[PDB]
Image (tube, rainbow, N blue to C red; front, side, top):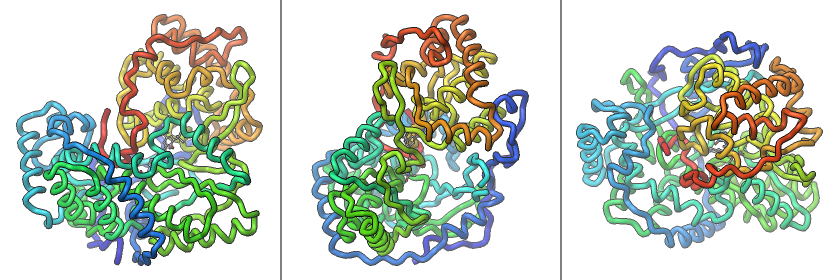
Length: 557
Ligand SMILES: COc1c(/C=C/c2ccc(NS(C)(=O)=O)cc2)cc(-c2ccn[nH]c2=O)cc1C(C)(C)C
């Protein structure tokens, strides 16, 4: 029951890859320890192949089937619709990988006759054949990190015509089913502010709270044929059109269960028998499976009043403590049950008794004060990876601007406000690119955002307090300051000095640029302005934001 079989053919790149941090005239103003930053390339794909390849054994008990029966009962209340070809076409990212059949993502988006005719033939083939394995491309992802080197992660995706078909059959399912099945435990329905609120309320709801995060080692490869057929049985509980039931059965049998792996040069690399990382159902499938195995493992471990918070393969559990030593034994039983379900741990879970010490989705809860001095909980993270990625993005244009996603999602943080905002607004001002729409990702979905709209977006997600937070925790300040020395980033005092200049430069431009100066950099001046709601913020169409997760799902809004 191997996750993969391999032929020995290499996982090949599509273009020239860089691993060393590119340097330009702006690099040193952000980060001096250049050797600390690197990008993963296809060159390390061979090491990843070794890591993701293993036998999976599954032992399914009554706790597993009990939880699954409960999930199916909630899934049976979902009604889902088929998207038209045109609706699914418009969800395609403009720079999505081109089809092998003579058309690209722009042809799909423009509803070109050639693209639409091929998509209709792919749809007809899904309905008429529910057996033939569908071809997939295997590629090494190019992602940036700080040292202490990770081998490249792999992406496995079917052809563009198939991806549009996945959307038609399952977009509405993967968008609506997880919240119905898991209720408040589904993490992707929350903005960062709502996530904090859920975590704090859950922690407060326990007499003696204990919490842990569970890290499954190589989650996609732990996903078995059983798991994928179980996911399909959940999707089939929905009230669906008969053509959608047939397409979902066909996509499960031909694509989701497994299939051949083809490199960028057209060679057969091998065969997958686990979760594909680049399909529409990756996020929803991972969330349902992680929640199912974890809920059953919570029952097997006799964990008391377990509240789960699940986002794909990321899991946080908050429960009632039975004292430190019993909690430690309980987590070892939880881990044993997860292992039997084919979800073994990477790092062993650690019980926590301070909400701020739990790391989930690479983040933790922290506290600052608003302008009235009131304590305000917000989400932050170690800024090492956002800063290494910001350094790369300082010298190279990339398809996804992590700096923009990080300013949006981490706007209340000390590090996103003082460093990311200051640095990228300085660069954009100098290039007169404040109005240029840039691509970023939020919960795996692609968005095209104009940096000039950042004050309005931040206000809608985090509220006006994101522009007034101060008196950050000693722990948070020290982690940020430690990260800056480690990477050779100028200290916060330099950033405050630079921000006064950036703020003045933005105010000089007037209009939307002045609003950026006013709201984003009010922290930098001694004579603070009283910030009031932005009228443009109410007009923002933030629908489609914080509904579901779409990592690897080829979704654009
Ligand atoms: C839910 O946690 C997040 C997440 C979580 C993302 C996430 C988590 C798990 C997975 N797993 S999978 C492959 O199986 O779908 C996939 C994506 C992402 C961001 C984020 C940061 C910057 N730019 N874009 C973003 O989406 C911020 C937060 C916080 C702030 C709410 C903690």
